[PDB]
Length: 224
Length: 213
Length: 193
Image 1: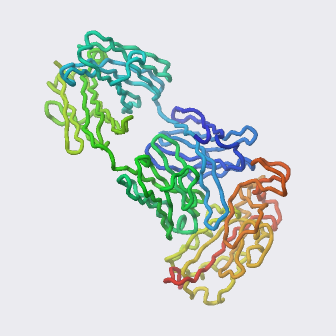
Image 2: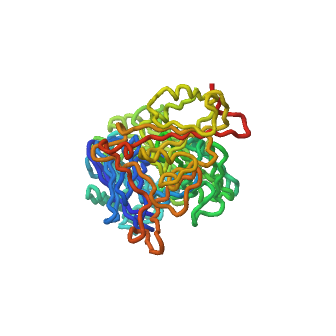
Image 3: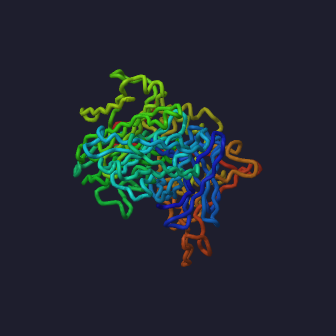
């Protein structure tokens, strides 16, 4: 998309985080830089602005000392930082270029938006997933078609991936979005739909990679 | 003050659709213009309309804007399925001394094949029970519309604690998928003779049941 | 009851190049409580009776607030020229309304400077009455290409006021409010006491 921000970020309560923004479709030229925040399932809120050429920063009242935005015209990059992170400040933070015009009711509009960098604040230290097999009950699923899967459990942070049989198995493979638990750890399930005749013959292994925890797990799913 | 938007509006393919953006005298009440953005789920917002009656090259011809007093309207004449998204309006507020957004509106194009859910239930594996943990898994897929309710029952009795369900999210085929997890202790799993997951969707209610045996 | 005080006793004011306007309708504007303060050094009205200020009905009443230097308040009047009047805020020759200003050095000035307040220094044409220009585009002076980057004859249209407690009253910050009255063919939303 239109400006390139940093990668995802996961932080503990009380930490501070700094994010970056670079330009696509432009060269930061005469564009004011804004920061807008989208809480989970919530509307957009603009917290800050930076004038690259003049190096003058204006922040919204809901902004406190906590948010501080700077920008280098030479480097072509723009930055923002937050301190004293808490549960509240979990969102996709956007950097966007403001545009102005001359007119009677002039109001700035954002023509270019970054990719979004989602910052998550949790007390959950990184943990590996527990992958248990979901044995197929050939008679309790479709006639002649079985449903077997894997249960990734208790993993933080969220990035995780599941491929069946080293990626050779794709049909019937439907992975489900992980859920967030009262503990703060994630858990998902990936099931596949296969013929019952191949249950005793074909071998089935889900391949899970939890890149944050650097954990790879292979588990065979055999019938009971 | 703030800008107010319909939380949700539904439209049929080909119909006109009118999304509102009303503000007090602090923002839209003065000359301050309104600006509209289209934002697909998971994508960064993109400018849709600036100055209300102007759209950047790349915004199709059916999007328009109008103003009359302290209100503002985004119109989609020939509604298409490519319009399912969030829509926010943006203007300036004098009391805020800054730009201001609206609540947003989700536009659901009501032109899709209604589909019944595919519920699949899994009992706690024997490997997990050794970990002093028991988890039931209720997979729901290929159901439209996306709104669904999940009720668990042990021995036909309603559940109370320990239930967590995900939010229906569209799949690759434009239908929706959701997951429900009943976390139990090993003693509770084997104590009850049958645990059941029940999923109601547009009157149709589907049930699956597992047993410790 | 008309809430005029909120714009006068506001925490933060806008920049002159991007002034803030607030409509004030459906209220009863008792201007007698506005003359209370002696703090408004420059209070001038244009086109209104001296006594009927509180005894008049107006369809609409707008407010326009911003911050400029003390010597530029003379430019907040019909038929004026200069950097503020041609490039930032222009009243019409037939203006109907008052103009209030007051010293805010005690608030809008920082040890070292408060450069957050800006003014437009370059513009090709003059601003039409009540037209706002917030274009942060490089100003081309003559025929030198800018490529969206500063250079010869290519300058950023905005510039910053350097407000410091140590500056002279002519260069100190002043907070301006331009109450502009409107009489339209419609029931008056704003009527005085």
